[PDB]
Image 1 (spheres, rainbow, N blue to C red):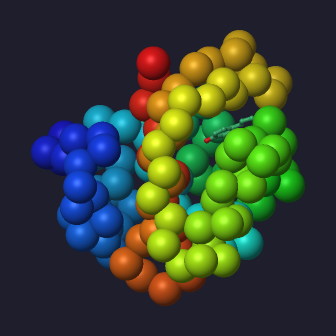
Image 2 (cartoon, protein in one colour):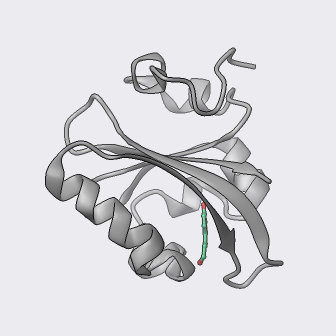
Length: 125
Ligand SMILES: *C(=O)/C=C/c1ccc(O)cc1
């Protein structure tokens, strides 16, 4: 396992340019999105939480295709505001309920260091 805690202040530096295999070593779910919400990376811990197959969701749009329950002001709205402003950093609880048992999580969205890239971190609550 990689020694990184959910919510750590410099998480974007520690994860920066992490390849797919190392991302799978994290204790929490990690997704990397472009500014439109297309999925660039999606780790094993996230797949274990959500049921999605990490290899198949790459390239899909998170808000339009994979996760319509997040297409709302409280999730997508916050994401796109942070993309538009270039500085996103927000943490909030949410319930995932699309075609799977409703599952409450804590979500941390934070702008990455790499261009046109934005992290969505997830753990169970
Ligand atoms: C609601 O539709 C949420 C769906 C979802 C959340 C997070 C994921 O990694 C995959 C699907």
